[PDB]
Amino acid sequence: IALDIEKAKVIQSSIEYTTLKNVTSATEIYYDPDPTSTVIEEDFDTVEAYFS
Amino acid sequence: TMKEITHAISSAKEQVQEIIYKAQHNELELKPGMTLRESFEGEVSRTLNDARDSAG
Amino acid sequence: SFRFCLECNNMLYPKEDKENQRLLYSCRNCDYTELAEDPKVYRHELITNIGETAGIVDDIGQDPTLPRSDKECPECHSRDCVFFQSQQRRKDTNMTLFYVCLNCKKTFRDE
Ligand SMILES: [Zn+2]
Ligand SMILES: [Zn+2]
């Protein structure tokens, strides 16, 4: 591994501490009374595709 | 020798100006573990120290 | 931006009607209740950009200590402009410049 940069980068990624806060860009809370559907039109397609 | 020293100092100032433009247009490479401002400051300091050493 | 009671002036808190399955904003010192229009009850931004270009005033062209450039204004196409870097001053702030013309005062960049 010492003489190969790719494996070294793999090890470096495996060691470094990473939390959800590191990758999270924003968080939101919504009111949505239908578990099988949604109010947001943007996320409607993905949730309906998941439910089907 | 004074014209050589003046030319070296002017060249270093031109290089620092180019680095300033590159940093202001987001074209500057970032040294790992350092922010954009820190990398910019380190590069400028290194350029100026090299300028003084060359003139001396 | 959050609303307040129209007769008590106190802050209206979100509430849910069990029987109606609707979101409502209800005051706590009064029985006033108003229907909620948007479902976004709460939003928190981990990475934010506000405060970067919002720091604009109409009379920023009267400052003599500000450098004057010759960048072309997209709106007025004037030959005189004043530029400054980001007002937000976090440790990881970019060094991009914001150019303000003396007629339209539109903020733009060279990117
Ligand atoms: Zn009230
Ligand atoms: Zn103008």
Image: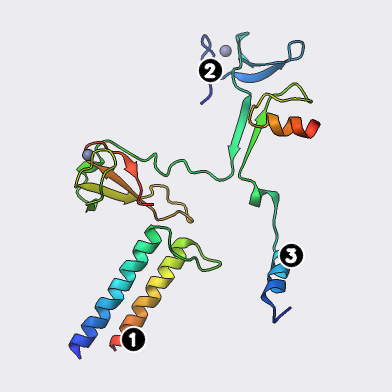
For residue C57, the mark is none
**Mark 1 = which residue?**
B53
In the image, residue A5 sits, relative to residue C86, either above or below, namely: below
Residue at x-position 74% and y-position 21%: A33
CA–CA distance between discs 2 and 1? 67 Å
Residue C73 appears at what percent x and percent y?
26, 44
Q: Amino acid at mark 3?
A: Ser
Residue at left offset 40%, top offset 77%:
B46
The spot of residue A6 in percent (x, y) is: 69, 72
SS category of the residue bearing label 3: helix
Q: Is residue A47 left or right of residue C8?
A: right
Disc 2 element: loop
Instruction: Give the residue number, with chain letter if any, for mark 2.
Output: C4
Tag count in the figure? 3
**Label 3: few (<14), some (14–19) or many (≥20) C-alpha neighbours in 10 Å:** few
Which is closer to the viewer, label 2 or label 3? Answer: 3
User: Do marks 2 and 1 share a subunit?
Assistant: no
Q: Is residue A37 left or right of residue A41?
A: right
**Helix, strand or loop for disc 1:** helix
Residue closer to the observer: B51 or B21:
B21
Which residue is at 37% across, 67% downward? Answer: B19
C26 or B38: nearer the viewer:
B38
Q: Are marks 1 and 3 in contact (CB under 8 Å)?
A: no
Of tags 2 and 1, which is closer to the observer? 1
Indicate whether A3 appears above or below B15. below
The quadrant of the rendering that contains the C terminus of chain B is bottom left
Residue B12's image quarter? bottom left
Q: Amino acid at mark 1?
A: Asp
Same chain shared by disc 1 and disc 3: no
The residue tagged 3 is A14
